[PDB]
Image: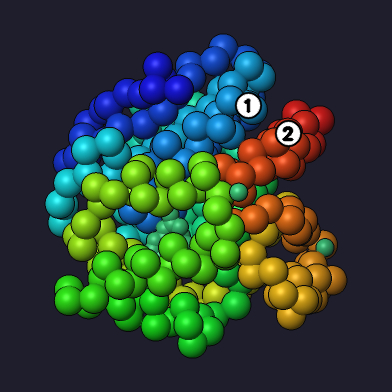
């Protein structure tokens, strides 16, 4: 719970982070938040993992229980932040697990840390193809100082997908309520730039200097054409796999924390046998 919350100076910035400080065999589980939310998204997943793993959740610049305005930064800076926390903490070997566009951090972290330190990754509910019209419009709305809130509302609609999902509604409407345009507009510029510059998550992962096992676990998009791009990518890359989780929303970490946990334990166990 909030018993594991700390704060430290990371270069210029005071960042909060979760660390259960569990004294156990590696690798540490590094749970990466997406944009404009914090460690609260992972409270149910931390419960699944707490007794068996050391679990660390960094919050990005301007993120946390008290969001704040900060200067412009991108996934590159998120990566330098994540590693500085891990260096301060004395963590060597880690398994990164990302929420959605936290994936840009995860894949760049894999490159930077290398396959000894970061031998595998798990990406959760991360749009594998380049932006379809509806999502591209969302990003344009987030970037708009007059329409960013409309932006979030449309994304909350897609994310909930017609479900009265109490815990996820709580996360979106309460736990993300204090994030403003400084975050949401940034999230729009960063994600748009990331696709523009890397093509896609699939292309970025394929382009790793050292490819290594990555699994995509997702609940949405729910249509067959999305499963198919995942299966086609998996057919093509030995190191890639996926699992459709069947959860109601964009936040499997919240709505199917037990399922997310068994995939993370599978990967952790594989690394230990290693
Ligand atoms: C927490 C979260 O999902 N954040 C995002 C914020 C803006 C745009 C997209 C996303 C996403 O990660 O899907
Ligand atoms: K319900
Ligand atoms: K495969």
**Mark 2 = which residue?**
265
Q: Are marks 1 and 2 in contact (CB under 8 Å)?
A: yes
User: Where is residue 34 drawn, in percent x and y?
Assistant: 43, 53
Q: Is residue 62 above or below residue 88?
A: below
Dividing the picture into quarters, in which one does residue 107 lie? bottom right
- Count neighbours of disc 2 (C-alpha within 10 A) and say few if under 14, some if 14 to 19, many if 20 or more: some
Image position, residue 102 (x, y; %): 47, 55
Q: Secondary structure at mark 2?
A: helix
Confirm whether residue 176 shows in the render. yes
Quadrant location of ligand 1?
bottom left
Determine whether, in the image, residue 208 is placed left or right of residue 145: right
**Element type at marker 1?**
helix
x, y percentage for residue 253? 58, 44
> At 60% across and 77% down in the image, what residue appears?
129
Q: Residue furthest bottom?
A: 133
Q: Is residue 109 visible?
A: no
**Residue at image point 54% right, 80% down:** 130
In the rendered image, which quarter contains the C terminus? top right
Density class for disc 1 (Cα within 10 Å; few <14, some 14-19, many ≥20) is some
Which of 155/117 is in front?
A: 155
- CA gap between label 1 and label 2 equals 8 Å
111 is higher (above) or lower (below) than 143: above
* Mark 1 lies on residue: 49
x then y, percent, for residue 269:
77, 31
Relative placement, left or right, of 125 versus 17 is right
């Amino acid at each position: 719970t909030d018993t594991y919350l700390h704060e430290t100076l990371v270069f210029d910035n005071k960042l909060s982070y979760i660390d259960n400080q569990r004294d156990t065999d590696g690798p540490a589980i590094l749970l990466l938040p997406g944009w404009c939310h914090d460690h609260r998204v992972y409270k149910y997943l931390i419960q699944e993992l707490d007794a068996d793993f050391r679990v660390i959740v960094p919050n990005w610049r301007g993120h946390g229980l008290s969001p704040s305005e900060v200067p412009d930064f991108g996934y590159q800076e998120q990566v330098k932040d994540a590693l500085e926390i891990l260096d301060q903490l004395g963590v060597e070997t880690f398994l990164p697990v990302s929420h959605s566009h936290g994936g840009w951090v995860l894949v760049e972290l894999l490159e930077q840390a290398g396959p000894e330190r970061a031998p595998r990754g798990i990406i959760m509910d991360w749009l594998m193809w380049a932006p379809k019209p509806d999502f591209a419009k969302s990003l344009t709305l987030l970037k708009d100082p007059e329409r960013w809130r409309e932006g979030t509302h449309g994304l909350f609609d897609v994310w909930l997908d017609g479900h009265d999902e109490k815990r996820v509604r709580h996360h979106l409407l309460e736990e993300m309520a204090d994030y403003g345009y400084d975050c949401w507009g940034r999230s729009g510029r960063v994600i748009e730039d990331a696709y523009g510059r890397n093509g896609s998550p699939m292309q970025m992962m394929a382009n790793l200097t050292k490819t290594r096992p990555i699994r995509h676990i997702f609940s949405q998009p729910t249509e067959p054409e999305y499963e198919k791009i995942n299966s086609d990518f998996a057919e093509q890359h030995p190191w890639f796999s996926y699992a459709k989780l069947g959860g109601p929303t964009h936040f499997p970490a919240i709505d199917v924390p037990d399922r997310a946990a068994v995939h993370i334990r599978e990967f952790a166990t594989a690394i230990r046998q290693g």
